[PDB]
Length: 218
Image 1 (cartoon, helix red, strand yellow):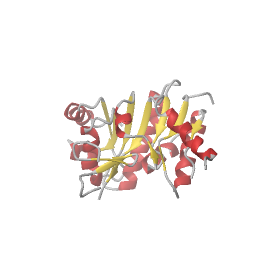
Image 2 (spheres, one colour):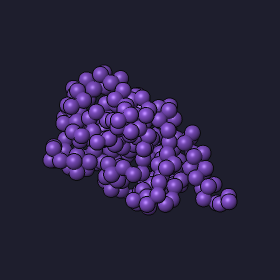
Image 3 (cartoon, rainbow, N blue to C red):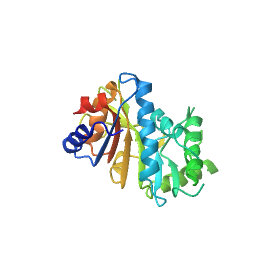
Image 4 (cartoon, one colour):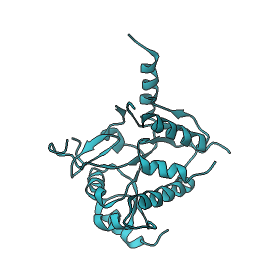
């Protein structure tokens, strides 16, 4: 870790982002090697930068976040709650289980979005209620390729353009921007335009990414 401190610094200045952490993948041009390096660095970050007062939201459909969780270990309370920030219909179950797994690890409550008033409407509002308490959002960044309209990428299935302007239960982009601390976890040469869009929209406060990606952005 920490082999690219100057690159981190330039990216922080270029994009007006607080923190960039740059990791080296074992296999620098491989998507899976990249996800595992980012996830591992993410696990460590959360081990040293998480507060017991933090209310965590996670983009549970993200495989990079899946990599983070699989790199962390099991005990006293390490957070206030873990809220699932995106839910859809089955995949969906695996995203629910991931959110739960993270709450178990942190020893805290989980707020989940499982997959003619009916109780499951109230379960959804329970999670929606939590969005306003969230203090640390952890999010993956998806690439597109909506496209023809202007979108290059998404956070939580919320799409944005090349400058980060916006173009299923999930947190909105406006709500995301105001969170105390948003951790982005993303790398891959295909994601650069998407990540720059997210950076330019001001959605991220911390980005953890690989060297090649950081150089593409840089």
